[PDB]
Length: 234
Ligand SMILES: [Cl-]
Ligand SMILES: [Mg+2]
Ligand SMILES: [Mg+2]
Ligand SMILES: [Mg+2]
Ligand SMILES: [Mg+2]
Ligand SMILES: [Mn+2]
Image (cartoon, rainbow, N blue to C red; front, side):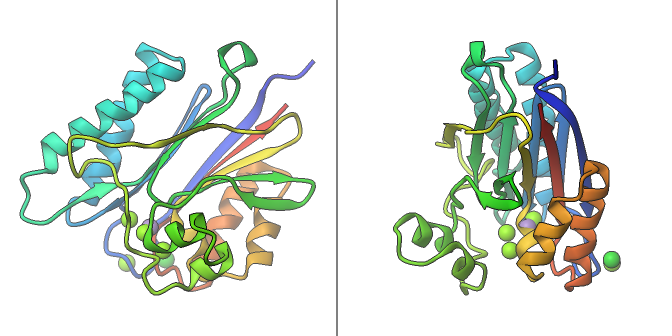
C-alpha cells in the first residue's frame, strides 16, 4: 500500500518587478508551508516565521503543537520587527498531513496565501483570505474570481508578526488518496489565466507542476513573488 504523502515539490520566483523575494516556503516531513512577507523587512518576517514554525512543530508534532508553533512564530516575528518605524509582517499557511489518529490533515492559515485541493481536474480554494477582498468572499458578497480584481485585494486583515496575538483559522482538510494539495502565495493568481494555472497545477510530475506554476505567473507579468508547494497524496 501507499504512503499518505507520495511526494512534494516547491518553487519560488521573485519575478521581474519586486526588488526582493519576501516569500518563503517549507516542505519537511508532513509539514508544508508558505509565508508571504510584506513591508521593508518582509523577508525577515517570512523566513523567521518558518524557521520558528519548523522548530516548534518538530518539538511537538501534533495539532496543538502546530498551533503553539504558529503562536511562537507570531511572537518571535513581533519581538524582532515590532519596533520598526513601519509595519512588516507575513502571511502563513501551514499544512500538516497528519494520519487519522492525529485527527487527519490540518491547515492553519493567516493572511492570503491559499490552500487549494486539486481533484479530478478541478482546483478549488479551501481557505479564506484575510484581506479586504477575501472578507467580502467570506461575507458572501463577491466571488473568489471577483476578489482577484478587487482594488483592495492587497490589504490584509490578519497577519503574523504585527502584534502579540493572532487568531489563525484552523480546520481539517477534506482530502484523500489521489488528491493534490497546493499552497501558494497570492502571486500565483495576480494575473494569469485561470485555465493555464490549472493546466500547470495538474502537471503529473509535481516538480514539473511547481516550475510551470511559477512560469505561468512570470509570463503573465510576474508583478509579485510567487511561491508554490505541491503535495501528492496516497
Ligand atoms: Cl523574472
Ligand atoms: Mg529584478
Ligand atoms: Mg510579499
Ligand atoms: Mg499580498
Ligand atoms: Mg496580490
Ligand atoms: Mn504576495
